[PDB]
Image (cartoon, coloured by chain):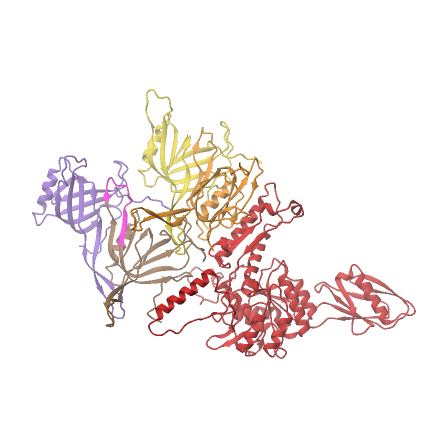
Chain colours: A brown, B purple, C yellow, D orange, E red
Amino acid sequence: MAVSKRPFSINSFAVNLNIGNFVDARYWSKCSKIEKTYNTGEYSDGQSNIIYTLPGAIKYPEVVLSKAFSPGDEELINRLIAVNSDPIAWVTVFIQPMYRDGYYNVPQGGKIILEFCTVARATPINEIDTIGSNAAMFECALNPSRIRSDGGNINWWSEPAAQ
Amino acid sequence: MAVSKRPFSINSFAVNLNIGNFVDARYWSKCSKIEKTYNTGEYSDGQSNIIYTLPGAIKYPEVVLSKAFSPGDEELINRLIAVNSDPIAWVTVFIQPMYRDGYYNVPQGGKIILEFCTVARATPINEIDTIGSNAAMFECALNPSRIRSDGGNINWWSEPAAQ
Amino acid sequence: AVSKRPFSINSFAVNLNIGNFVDARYWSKCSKIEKTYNTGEYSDGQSNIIYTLPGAIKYPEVVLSKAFSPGDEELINRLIAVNSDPIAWVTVFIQPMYRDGYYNVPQGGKIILEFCTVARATPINEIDTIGSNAAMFECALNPSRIRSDGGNINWWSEPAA
Amino acid sequence: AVSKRPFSINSFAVNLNIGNFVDARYWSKCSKIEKTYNTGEYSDGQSNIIYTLPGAIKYPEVVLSKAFSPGDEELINRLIAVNSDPIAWVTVFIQPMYRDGYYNVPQGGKIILEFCTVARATPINEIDTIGSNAAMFECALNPSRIRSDGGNINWWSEPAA
Amino acid sequence: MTNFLNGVNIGTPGAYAFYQTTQSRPINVEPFRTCYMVGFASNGVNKNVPTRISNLTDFTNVYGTSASTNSVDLFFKNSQGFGNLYFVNVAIPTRYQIVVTAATAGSYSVTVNGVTKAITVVGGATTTTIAADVISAINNDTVLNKEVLATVGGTSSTVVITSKKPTNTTTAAVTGVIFTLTTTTGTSPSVADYVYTINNTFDPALEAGFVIAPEAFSTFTKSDRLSIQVALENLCSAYRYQWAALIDSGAMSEISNTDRAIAEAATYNSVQGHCSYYYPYLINLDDQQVPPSAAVAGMALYRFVIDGFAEPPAGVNFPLKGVKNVAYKVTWEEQNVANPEGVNCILNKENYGIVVWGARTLSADPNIVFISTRIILNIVINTLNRGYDFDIFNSVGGTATVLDNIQRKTNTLLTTLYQAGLFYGQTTSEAFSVLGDASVQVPSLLQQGLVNMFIWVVPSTIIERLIINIKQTAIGDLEATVALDTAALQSSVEEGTATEGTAPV
């Protein structure tokens, strides 16, 4: 009916972390998929032989962040390694969608916030090879507990349970 | 923002071994990832139906070093084969990051030390093929117990645990 | 209405800054200067037309060439060592000018390729004891940004709000 | 017996609309203009002949070129930034005409490539300090639709309704 | 606007809090999100000057008392900060009444704005003849005929000189005993003053939008209401504005029922449908019957922002806020007779509220029946005019590239409107077409400075009546019945035989 705006690209997001009480200013170039999965059970109404699906046991799957391993990542390594040691502490992931050309980010809407994440894997070095040419990749797996949306004119994620 | 210090490459690390009481001068060409893996369980707070992840049972996964099988590696073979025979002997892995152009390494920071590693596999010859042209690969799999760093001015693997 | 004539392919002067070193040598050949958009494909679901989504900008490799001449040994030794320092970058300056002999007429600023890394250095293109071509120094650079801030034309400007 | 001479390859004027600004510059070279059907293969089972099924229309990339001349800095700075705005598009206007000198004789509307995105901007095709060719500005566009409603022939009507 | 300057008058560094006041919504410059209200206020601050109003408080502060206060309040309540309101205070012209006492013979003169007219009286003269001579001299003078108008007052021995330019200073004086001067000025504006303000106060550069005169329509009589309707029709259909006007019924005591509203609308004429008539006065929360226009316009501008600019000021989804009831209950049959005649009813639907249940114009042209089409055409025209304003007064060099550039700009603007959704068609080729190149420009006209552009558009339509044709099927045969009937219906629509027939009541 009308083609007004281009869609978001796969490069159209900025990823930041809050590790415990530390507001880490480093950015992550890659993030894995973001979902709300429903574990399912099968049932019948007894009046047919069709298998129905019963949603339950919501889960937000693992999110893998990755970036280029650079000096100044020692604070990142130590903070991610130590965050799980404090039962009160957990990681927050801020994803800001945007329509950046170069360094010309134009963010619209709020940020998708993965709230209450626990570290499951910290990989400062993905691989070593004296003949390899790729950039060493810092990797970090996180298990989020909730997703919300904060700031901005557009709310991306809102859960219903409580009204 | 501004890329001031170009990130580390996967060829930007030098790997050395301490087999028991022996300090081996041989340098290795490859190494797998260095990680702090958290085993995880599932739970619920009861007042909702989201699956929450509980970390536990720390583990540092197996690390596979590899180099080119060259003369003078027979001492390395014998030491790696015999190290596990002594319940007191351990294998230590030293990884020094560095920005090597050629032979022009410039180290920065200490060295990531995998402490108290046990040999799980020693493969002097990856395979034999009289038509093959690849260099024969020496491989060694190690199971580390701890990770630290002490020989420089960065200290990028500080755990809060040890004594 | 032919007034101002267009730039000729020889209407540019090329200079380098190699780390903290400013080289006074000039380069007589440079490849295309470009901004490339790597493209993905998508659909709106309302039609079977393929749409192109730009992203992942990259400035492709630029190959400079000049005549291999005495006094190029320091240029060689600097280009070899640039990458050894993770904080050293090559900077390429292209000045457009209406040149006639040694008479230049620069107008506008100089297009600057910033934060370039050396990917290849070829002091000698080839050797032929009965050849007659001039030996050509070549050097390939991977740039990371293009700007311009001299002169009065600002050839290249990025949206920066 | 030919009553009307056919169009020459020089019989078209090319213009650009970049975002909300109208460019006064003309382009001297444009590549092929197409409507391409991506094809699948199938069978009716009645025979072993391979049948072709059209689908997934696409208008292939169009490469415009012109002589890099002063006053092209504005065009550069706009083509670089057009993609930065998801609302902005590049629109290409091709007016066929019979020209001898500056005496173009247009007939019919103009082919309009609408909703085009920049995939490549090459201000300088190459540099050769002893070369003689004119420097060629180049631009690559990924059109999404083609129409024509500027005149009295309408040679690119879709099957709309 | 506010919420940002709180920490400006603090010199100390630190962190403070200020409890967040209200923030204004800035309204953009889309050609059709403004409403111009022509009203009167004895406080003549902005006589015949369209002034932006931020809110009802600003209106009261500037203009004080005014019969348009209720309409302004309704507009702001319904617009909810969207759209702009421009008030036009009608200027009351100066007036000078000269009574000619007798026919005394002699030489006298009459002064108007410093221009003196000598008048000579001889034997056989009369008061009426002298007054007529003065009127003729003033009206046939080349200078005064444009500044003022001279007519006969309530007596043949009286002359009334009315300022033809209300804002300008008008002065009169006499040189003669028979002429007795008196200064006068209607303490309230009249229909002629309203007509002048309507016809001579709107700069085409002004943002397009709605035009309303609720005070005039509520106060004036039938003849004056017709005159003001004609003035608004001429304004909105003028080739320079192409706006839309909202006409209201008279006072409900006069237009008691729907038949009288139909008669008044029938008297009203709008060939191209620039004027749209509404009837029930909207009793607000303070129980005052306020002419519909302002409330409707407020809702319209709000709807334009939310629903869309192709959406007409109507619907149950977009009701009316700030009111509680309608001054009259329109029956279904009354509305059935009225709506085809151009009367847009406002109804108190239960479970919806006060809703405008009409979107028709006063035109007899079937192509511009709905006000949405009129608004779409006005938006197109005004967008193009604003775009070309920057192209006016531009040299036409040798290339004649300005005509090409104008076609380029037209294509861009019409594509923007297409994305906005104002046209019927899946593609721009289905939506619109332009022709403005040099092939249609004549050098003779170019020498005078004329450029001709030709544009074709296909405005979107709306859903007015939805017809449900559903059949009651016996148990078992639903699939076969549906297959057969659907085949028949699809075939008829495809081959174009669906329309062939007689429309039933």
Residue E215 seen from this side: no
Q: Is residue E442 left or right of C62 when viewed as pictured?
A: right
The answer to which of E178 and B144 lies nearer the viewer is E178
Tell me if residue D57 comes above or below residue D100 in the rendering. Answer: below
Which quadrant of the structure image shows residue C22? Answer: top left
Stretch in magenta: A128-140
Residue B86: x %, y % from top left:
7, 48
**Residue at the front extreme of this rendering:** D46
Tell me where residue D107 appears, x and y as whole percent: 55, 43
Q: Position of B145 compared to E78: left or right?
A: left
Q: Which residue is pictured at 78% across the width and 74% down the height?
A: E154
Residue A20 drawn above or below residue E348: above
Q: In the depicted view, which residue is nearer to us: E8 or E206?
A: E206
Say if the magenta span includes residue D108: no
Answer with the quarter of the image where residue E170 lies. Answer: bottom right
User: How many numbered tags mark residues here?
Assistant: 0
Percent across and percent down for residue E173 are 81, 66
Front position in the image: D108 or A163:
D108
- Residue E302 visible in the shown view: yes
Q: Nearer the viewer, residue D6 or E471?
A: E471
Q: Residue at x 82, y 72 (%)?
A: E156
Q: Position of residue E400 (x, y in %)?
A: 59, 43
Q: Please indicate whether residue A64 sits to the left or right of residue B21 in the image.
A: right
Is E268 above or below relative to C42? below
View extreme (right): residue: E123
Q: Is residue E405 left or right of residue C112?
A: right
